[PDB]
Image (tube, rainbow over all chains, first blue to last red; front, top):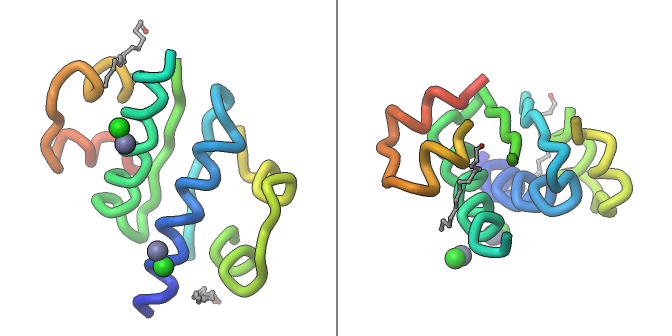
Length: 29
Length: 29
Length: 21
Length: 21
Ligand SMILES: [Cl-]
Ligand SMILES: [Cl-]
Ligand SMILES: [Zn+2]
Ligand SMILES: [Zn+2]
């Protein structure tokens, strides 16, 4: 699923913005 | 620190590609 | 997971905040 | 952390793998 892989690339970029200094864990399916 | 944040943006993208289905954890300083 | 929720529908920044530490 | 190790020097793919889950 290429589009799923492409979507996850934007998701981690989005998380890095919102979470900031708090950090985050990325746990896909 | 803006330069640190710019590097972190590329940090998250590289981890997403390298780690794959395992996922990754990111935490700034 | 985040892929299920946010790749099937648009997630706002507030919705994405739930996945932060 | 990853920022200290990899924003001061170029980290290889294997070095980045240390921060996977
Ligand atoms: Cl895309
Ligand atoms: Cl840059
Ligand atoms: Zn894209
Ligand atoms: Zn850049």
